[PDB]
Image 1 (cartoon, rainbow, N blue to C red):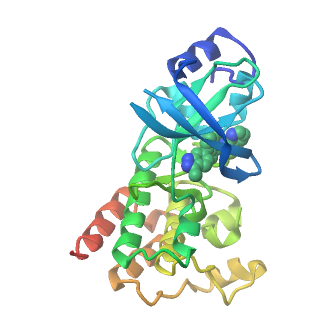
Image 2: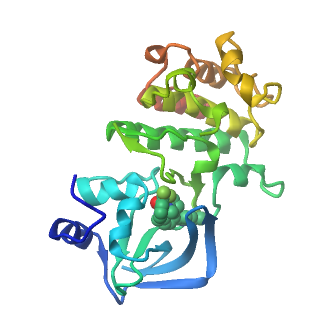
Image 3: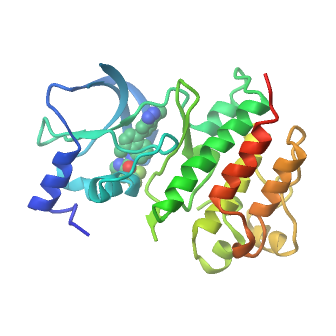
Length: 277
Ligand SMILES: Cc1ccc(-c2ccc3c(C)n[nH]c3c2)c2c1[C@H](N(C)C(=O)c1ncccc1C(F)F)CCC2
């Protein structure tokens, strides 16, 4: 509720709670590790102990009202941190004309690119483990009243230790590609944790196919009509039977009947547990 778009004492104090000192951050301007509609994100060094980080500059501190709600929520609610959620490390106010927003560094980038890379060899166990990590991150987001709205493998990041973090690029909200949306979202534009559970099922399917495009047999214009006839994504070749049953539960047409993220954590933890060695 505090104003993040105009200078006021509440905004200044909230940002100070997450300040990174002027001698604590170094931006490696020649190492662009993120590019998109938002511009560039640079690799950096955070002095706490030397740690890798990712830095996005702003034109001024009042531009913080325009960044992801994962970052904005942490500053406002003071309690937002989970190993499987990509959130704020801090903000460096060293230059008034260039405040620096800093997040953790994820070496392997976006999960979809990682699993599509022909040089990488993640096993089925690794892929299912990435799915379990996403469900734990989402279970935490759901507990915080967050609705992701764009859950897909391209929005999940993978770090050097193989920790997956659910990332947000401006669409999450405290409470789109059509082939990831729940039926009731395609029909009524309503988004809840249950519509994220539907996107999660699609995410699992992306992991089991190593990033294949969903519904190769269905045009974008016909996806809703296809789902209305009870049709769903087919079981990928290396997907265990109980994992596909979990996927089908995620795509139940009645939102109330889909499992919660806590139950997904439990079911996927039991399947992942069978991958020994
Ligand atoms: C601020 C920020 C800092 C570092 C990253 C990042 C990137 C890559 C890596 C990699 C590869 N590892 N770690 C990384 C961190 C990102 C952001 C993102 N972001 C740009 C914003 O929230 C944002 N900012 C300004 C205006 C609008 C928005 C919003 F609408 F998208 C959220 C996720 C990416």
